[PDB]
Image: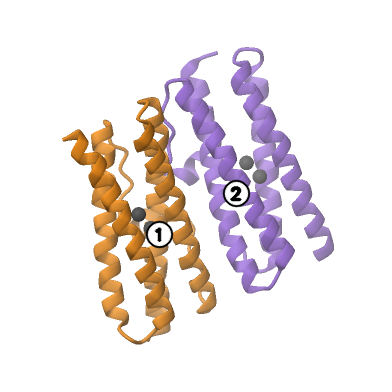
Chain colours: A purple, B orange
Amino acid sequence: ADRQTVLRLLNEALATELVCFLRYKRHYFMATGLKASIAAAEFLEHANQEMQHADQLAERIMQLGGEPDFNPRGLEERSHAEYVEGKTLKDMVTENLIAERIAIDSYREIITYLGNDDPTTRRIFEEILAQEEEHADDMADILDDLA
Amino acid sequence: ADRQTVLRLLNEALATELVCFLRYKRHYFMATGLKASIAAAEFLEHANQEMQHADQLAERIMQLGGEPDFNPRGLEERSHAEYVEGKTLKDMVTENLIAERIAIDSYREIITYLGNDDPTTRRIFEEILAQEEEHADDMADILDDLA
Ligand SMILES: [Fe+2]
Ligand SMILES: [Fe+2]
Ligand SMILES: [Fe+2]
Ligand SMILES: [Fe+2]
């Protein structure tokens, strides 16, 4: 694989995970204000899992001799997912489902781009992808009870 | 106290803690690349403590009927501390000491501004201030062994 291209894709994924962490933290706090207990619990669980994903990505960046970009200024422009506050609980759940589906689609594209060229990095994306699918299922379950 | 002014100061402190979290996470990963084990450990411990501070601040914002601003785009402009990468270990340690001293000075100013007008919020800042003093001592201890 091209080392620089893999490092850029890892840093884009890192930005995605950090944006999703911040968005889920926002939603957790707002959900506590609505007394939406299980939604809040899922938002916080998901936030901490996104930070675990960020950690795995940054560790791989270090292993490949790159530098992980945690600068908040450019995060949104490196991330495929958006930071969106929303107003209602339904808005927040919908925005998280949108973001998880974006992350899923982006990680599938990265896995295909990598092919057989960097198996270690590929497996990291495969593991994260599987957990984003669980995140999306979690959000869909809540969203269906709000429709 | 003026509720809106207290909410703004809480959101500025929240941004400060989030910037410091991101900067310490950057430094942790770079320090692992340098095999600077105890510096890395302190950077990560400090990062997770800054996120605990952020959580306490956001919880108080919710209690006062405000909204905690986790948007990464404007974080640096709301934060008194800066996100600074540095190049060497000494640079990173120095930047964290600078940032802790900034946070300490800003939190002392906030505590004086609050006076007796919002004791709950004041005590939150007092608790965080005490831990930032410990963070600064930790960084100074490392920095002196690098001088
Ligand atoms: Fe993730
Ligand atoms: Fe996710
Ligand atoms: Fe702090
Ligand atoms: Fe600190």
Between circles 2 and 1, the one closer to the viewer is: 2
Residue drawn where x is 83% and y is 59% of the image: A144
Residue under pointer 2: A48
When the figure is inspected, residue A147 is found, relative to residue A12, above or below; the finding is below
Amino acid at circle 1: Ala
When the figure is inspected, residue A28 is found, relative to residue B91, above or below; the finding is below
Relative image position of residue B118 (x, y in whole percent) = 39, 83
The front one of B137 and A99 is B137
Residue drawn where x is 59% and y is 22% of the image: A121
The front one of B65 and B104 is B104
Relative image position of residue A123 (x, y in whole percent) = 66, 24
Q: Are marks 2 and 1 on the same chain?
A: no
Relative image position of residue B142 (x, y in whole percent) = 26, 40
Chain letter of the residue beneath label 2 in the structure image: A
Residue drawn where x is 69% and y is 34% of the image: A129
Q: Residues within 10 Å of mark 1 (few under 14, many from 20)?
A: many
Residue drawn where x is 70% and y is 43% of the image: A101
Relative image position of residue A92 (x, y in whole percent) = 66, 61
Q: Residues within 10 Å of mark 2 (few under 14, many from 20)?
A: some
For the N terminus of chain B, the quadrant is bottom left
Q: Taking the image as drawn, is residue B134 in sight?
A: yes
Q: Quadrant of ligand 3?
A: bottom left
The front one of A76 and B55 is B55
Side of A104 where A50 appears, left or right: left
